[PDB]
Structures are given as structure tokens and as C-alpha cells.
Image 1 (cartoon, rainbow over the protein chains, first blue to last red):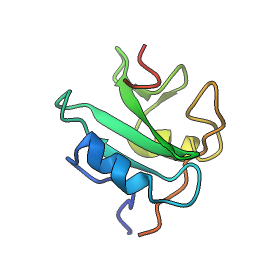
Image 2 (image 1 turned 120 degrees about the horizontal axis):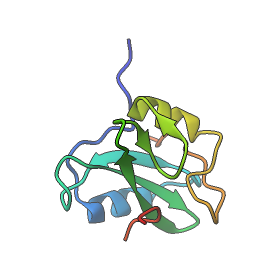
Image 3 (image 1 turned 135 degrees about the vertical axis):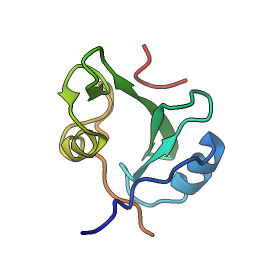
Amino acid sequence: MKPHPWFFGKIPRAKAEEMLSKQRHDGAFLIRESESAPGDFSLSVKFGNDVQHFKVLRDGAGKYFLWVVKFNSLNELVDYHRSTSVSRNQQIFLRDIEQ
Amino acid sequence: XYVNVX
């Protein structure tokens, strides 16, 4: 198969912002491993000229989520948010980076 | 920070 082009591993928050601020399309994102919280994943995404950061949460049942809908994998969370906004105030749909 | 916390 093909590996996922959105997983960037352990990269700083500032480095994700520098990279995403240079993307052209709204929704360009990456998943990175948080340095502030070891073991947590951070979803960094571009909207307008800004770069917003979302913490990938895990509930008591071990399911991943951003708000209320629960997923069995990061892969499913990411794919679901290609057509459902990651934000409750803005319409930010995840779309792959131009590598 | 994080838009979704809390």
C-alpha cells in the first residue's frame, strides 16, 4: 500500500506553523507528535493566513475524537474531517499538503 | 492553545 502523507512525527509547533503558512489552500494540514504532551498527537491546519492547532483526544473507551464523534483510528478521524469541519466556528475541511 | 481544549 501507500503510507499517509499527513503524518510528520515529532516536529515543533512553530515548525508546523512555518510550513503550513506557506500552503495555498484552506484546510492544508498535518498530524505531528506533541512535544508539550508526550504521547499526544496534534492536528495543525491552515485557515486563511492562520495556522490552528487541535489536540487529538482519546476518551475512556480509547477512541480518538476532536469534539463529540468518536473514531477507532487517527486514519478514520482524519478521513471523516475531509468533509466535516474540524472547527465549530469556522468551516475548515482537511486536505493534503502539496509536497 | 488548542482550539478544541476544553
